[PDB]
């Protein structure tokens, strides 16, 4: 509270660490459904069903232009990619399984890097 400060974690390396994790996700062989925005003119249903589209190239642009205030807002956008994927794809489809695999991959890197 006012003039009563908690100790806080060193956040000076957060930007570089998030960039490294995002590079690892960009180069994963199962990243292909998530590298660019879904084409809203060509994919039936996506625009109406998915209220907040997100993809790796959009996250990369936001990270490069100072649009994440902290590392938690970055992780929210990554998780949104995989939450959208589950909403729109059957678990046993190629895209569905790719999403489950990438979520698992991300959360381990996240835990190992920051927790
Ligand atoms: C990411 C995703 O849900 C998705 C769906 C359909 C596509 O043709 C490409 C990507």
Image: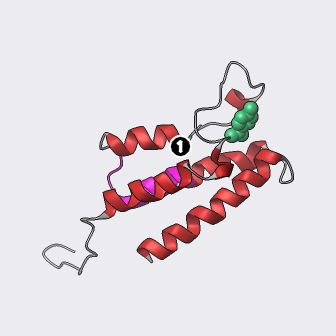
Please report the residue visible at 43 percent of the width from the left and 43 percent of the height from the top. Answer: 60
Q: Is residue 68 visible?
A: yes
* SS state under label 1: helix
Provide the residue span drawn in magenta. 67-78
In terms of image quadrants, where is residue 6? bottom left
Position in image of residue 98 (x %, y %): 73, 52
Q: Can you identify the residue that label 1 sits on? A: 56
In the picture provided, is 43 more to the left or to the right than 6? right
The tally of labels here is 1
Q: Residue at x 74, y 46 (%)?
A: 87
Q: Where is residue 62 in the image (x, y as percent from the top left)?
A: 39, 41
Residue 33, horizontal then vertical, whole percent: 68, 41
Question: Observer-nearest residue: 16 or 87?
Answer: 16
Residue 74: horizontal and vertical position, in percent? 44, 54
Q: Which residue lies furthest to the top in this view?
A: 41
Nearer to me, 96 or 45: 96
Magenta segment's dominant SS is helix
The residue at 54%/48% (across/down) is: 26
Would residue 4 be found to the left or right of residue 90 on screen? Answer: left
Q: Is mark 1 within 8 Å of ligand 1?
A: no
Q: Is residue 63 magenta?
A: no
Taking the image as shown, residue 109 lies to the left or right of residue 63, namely: right
Q: In which quarter of the image is the N terminus?
A: bottom left
Quadrant occupied by the C terminus: bottom left
CA neighbours of label 1 inside 10 A, class few (<14), some (14 to 19), many (20+): many
Residue depicted at x 56% and y 50%: 27
Residue occupying the far left of the picture: 3
Name the quarter showing ligand 1: top right
Residue 47 appears in which quarter of the rendering? Answer: top right
Residue 49 in sight in this render: no
């Amino acid at each position: 509270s006012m003039s009563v400060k908690k100790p806080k974690r060193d956040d000076s390396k957060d930007l570089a660490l998030c960039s490294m994790i995002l590079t690892e996700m960009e180069t994963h062989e199962d990243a292909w459904p998530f590298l660019l925005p879904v084409n809203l003119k060509l994919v039936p249903g996506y625009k109406k069903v998915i209220k907040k589209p997100m993809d790796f190239s959009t996250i990369r642009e936001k990270l490069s232009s100072g649009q994440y205030p902290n590392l938690e807002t970055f992780a929210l956008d990554v998780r949104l990619v995989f939450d959208n994927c589950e909403t729109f794809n059957e678990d046993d489809s190629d895209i569905g399984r790719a999403g489950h695999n990438m979520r698992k991959y991300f959360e381990k890197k996240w835990t190992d890097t920051f927790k």
